[PDB]
Every structure is written in structure tokens, then in C-alpha cells.
Image (cartoon, rainbow, N blue to C red; front, side, top):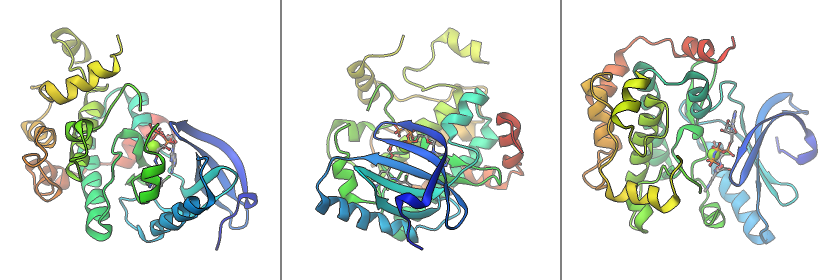
Amino acid sequence: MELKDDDFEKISELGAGNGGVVFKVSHKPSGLVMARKLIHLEIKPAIRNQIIRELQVLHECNSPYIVGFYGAFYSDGEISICMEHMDGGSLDQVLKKAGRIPEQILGKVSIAVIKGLTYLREKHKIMHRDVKPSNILVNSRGEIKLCDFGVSGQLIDSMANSVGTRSYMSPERLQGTHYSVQSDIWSMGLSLVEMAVGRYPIPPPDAKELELMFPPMAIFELLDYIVNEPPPKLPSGVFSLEFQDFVNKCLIKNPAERADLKQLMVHAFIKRSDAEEVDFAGWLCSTIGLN
Ligand SMILES: Nc1ncnc2c1ncn2[C@@H]1O[C@H](COP(=O)(O)OP(=O)(O)NP(=O)(O)O)[C@@H](O)[C@H]1O
Ligand SMILES: Cn1cnc2c(F)c(Nc3ccc(Br)cc3Cl)c(C(=O)NOCCO)cc21
Ligand SMILES: [Mg+2]
């Protein structure tokens, strides 16, 4: 069934950020609760049709590790993407409420991210391009799913400009055009360290700030750090050697030396997490108040 603007009714706002705002909406004709992302783009009709056209491939991105798509359309200066509502939010949200995220949980997340990236690359030859904690969604059934990946090339173009004071970009992507899918591996590694530790891990915590857990940077100052200083590490002692090596291999500055999806999928840490009996659903609601 096709989706139009007037068949929707707003319920609440799930949040916003940089070029988009997403609402919890009711799709009146079907009764479904959806998440509807609005993206403002002053752009000619010819290209917006192509964006809408390109976004349709989301209809065949079906995976337990990828957020469900309902449909895409154009309202007034607004491109709408309608998706599965994830009643548990983004990992960046659960991080706030949780402080830190336990290694074993992070292990299940790692599993989901790899399978998600693998699915998108394997079955669609598509690179994510924006891996970070806000674009990993979770829900009360304990599903862990990726969103906001770069499915439409023209959207990639039309969003080219508009970034902030926290980069999840690989150093190769920061420095030039010589980047690709290995960049997502970096984005993952960093995200993990962040969720693991309780904050964006650059710059890395001083001697003091570390034993406590257990000013914001200038733009250039931060990017300069990412590309020229050694990458962040999981602090020793509080995380299994397995986890440490995993993130370490994810955060190699040289993208050709950096681990790939193939390799991470059979890494000691994944295989260990793969076996671990973890009630992720239970932990989720427990730490954010719910079911
Ligand atoms: N399908 C969804 N279900 C539930 N909540 C969602 C969904 N999609 C997005 N959200 C929420 O909307 C918030 C903002 O979304 P979004 O416009 O993609 O920006 P962001 O990921 O937060 N930061 P940025 O990537 O810099 O734009 C996210 O942090 C989520 O909390
Ligand atoms: C660059 N680019 C190319 N295609 C894209 C695309 F489809 C996007 N959205 C999206 C994708 C899959 C699913 Br499932 C759900 C959504 Cl909402 C986003 C995106 O929403 N970036 O979020 C930034 C903040 O608003 C970006 C895309
Ligand atoms: Mg986003």
C-alpha cells in the first residue's frame, strides 16, 4: 500500500539531529505505528524524484539486523522515510540512561553490527557511511538493528555539506577521498569504545579520569588528533583481552591493515560473545524503564 502525508497523524517526537527529525506517527489506514523521518531539502523535483526512486531499494533490505522500511515519499520540502518504530531507541540514548554498556552486551551489539554491514555489502553492495551509536536502534524484543545507511547515491550528494564536535569518521575519510567500506569498521570500533567507556573516547581519558569511572575540543584540534595521534584503546584490566584486541583491530589507522568484516566475524571476541547466553531484552528495559 502507498504512503501519503495526510494518512499520518503525529504521536510524539522521537528526536532530531542534523538534517533530519523523526516522529512517532500513526499510519491511520493500516493502524501501524511507524517512525517517520523528515529530511528538509530545497532541491529541484527531478533530483527529489530520483532520491525517492533510489530509496525504494530499502523495500528489499530485509534483515533482523536492519531496520524495517515501510515507504518513502515527498511532502513539502520534506522527504519522508517511514520505518519500523524501535521502542528502545538508539544506543546513544541507552548509553545516556545507562552510563556504560557492559562488555557482554556490547558483544551482542558487535555481532549485530557486523551482520548488518555484511548484509548490506553482501546482498546490496552498499556501504553504511554513518556508523555511530545513534544509528544503531534497539527494541524490547532484543533486536539490534542498523539504520540511516547510505542507500541512495543522490542523497549522499545532496547531503554532502552540513558535522559538529564528534567525528566517527575514519582518518582516511577525514583526510581525503581515498576511502571505502573499511571506514565503517573504524566507525564501529570507536562507537564500541565510546559505549564501553561512557563517553566519546577522544581525547582518551587521563590517568585520573580513568580510575574515577571505575573542556570540549576545537574542531581542527579534534580531527588533528584522530588522524595523527595513536588511536584509542580499551583500558587494560576492566575488559577481557579478547575485547581489547577486537577494538584494536577495528581501529588500525591504515585501512588495508585494519580488520575486515570477514575477519572480525571469526574473531575470538565475536565467537565468545556468539556463545554467551545473554538476556539483552531484559537488560534493555531494566536499564531504561519499560516492559
Ligand atoms: N526508527 C526509529 N525508531 C525509534 N527511534 C528513532 C528511529 N529513528 C530515529 N530515531 C530517533 O531519532 C533520533 C534522531 O535521529 P537522526 O535524525 O537520525 O539523528 P541522530 O542519529 O540522532 N544524530 P545525526 O546522525 O548527527 O543526525 C535518534 O537518536 C533516535 O533517538
Ligand atoms: C546519505 N544517505 C543516503 N541514503 C540515506 C538514507 F536512506 C538515510 N535514511 C535511512 C536509511 C535506511 C533506513 Br532503514 C532508514 C533511514 Cl531514515 C539517511 C539518513 O537518515 N541519515 O541520517 C542523518 C540525519 O538525518 C541517509 C542517507
Ligand atoms: Mg541519524
